[PDB]
Image 1 (cartoon, rainbow over the protein chains, first blue to last red):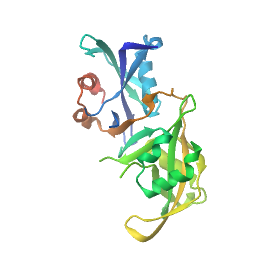
Image 2 (image 1 turned 60 degrees about the vertical axis):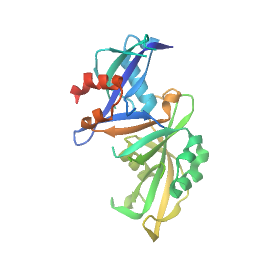
Image 3 (image 1 turned 180 degrees about the horizontal axis):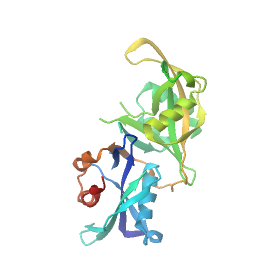
Image 4 (image 1 turned 135 degrees about the vertical axis):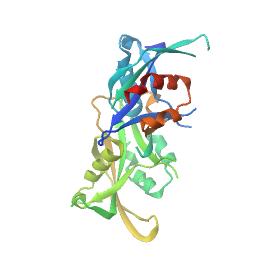
Length: 125
Length: 141
């Protein structure tokens, strides 16, 4: 269902109450940082912005709206592989965040207080 | 009324539901001991229902609109820098509200996230592809 060599990048930001903006960066847990990226589906070929919005929600949980679409650019893979990237600005501070499957939460907790909260409520999941 | 209770806190275990019924849980840590759920003080006018504090703190810390799905009995912990201090903690499950549910793929977990100011973005990018995207679009900010 994905186009193998066509990707979308979402530069995700939000406006704060004091009128300023902040930009979301990501990395795979475990280079520096990156924006949101994903393959464009075949049924998204005609509007890659739809892919940028879908990927933003998949990765972050926020629903977004394309504010600007940049010109496509090409990058190598296999150096013969040519990937076409469609970049977009997508509008949706102190802490770093991470989404985790429930079976992996306990291994991330090191504080007694957090472990106690999880011990009382984990059977919801 | 909206003054914080010094020794009463709410914890929110924030989660989202994916379209197939799978669930993922949000963790956080101060940039720079492990990970943690959302935590903050309960206000005087929230003491009768600390779930209100859990919803408020979730919004403040993450930007998500949440709904309380479950809340555990209160538990007690000592003060972090004072063993005489007694803190009562009210833990909650809080579901992130979304217009539509995302597909369950491995894109939905194992990515660490950080919000930065536009002026800090470039120094965190190391890959040509990301730098190119930023070079084309940074004039928006």
